[PDB]
Image (cartoon, rainbow over all chains, first blue to last red; front, side):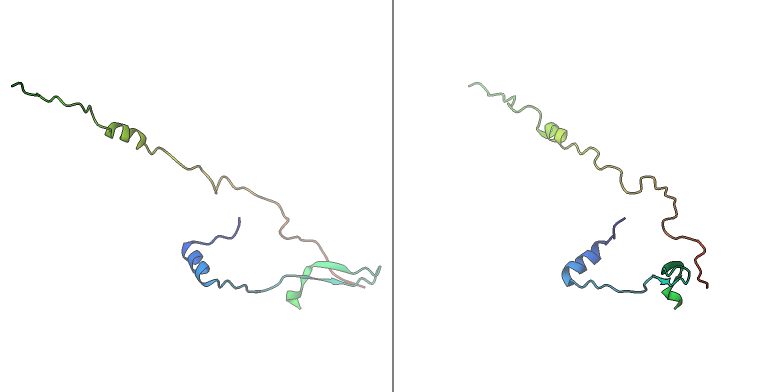
Length: 51
Length: 53
């Protein structure tokens, strides 16, 4: 489903042209080094939210 | 002299033909909700992924 806007907000947008965008939080993972084979691998469990 | 009598020339009224086209009928088609099911795990995963020596 695409984003929906009702009537009054549509009128206010076409009048004021003020539509801002906020970045609340960002999900994302860490890849760690492996001492076994040197390959840096992503842990999908851990995220930067912990860190 | 002889009276006209006047029986008139106009017959009925357009109003019946006007009412014919005046027909509105039924418009628009079903949309949006449909059925909606959906089930799979492409959203989040779960598998042991720790680190060690």
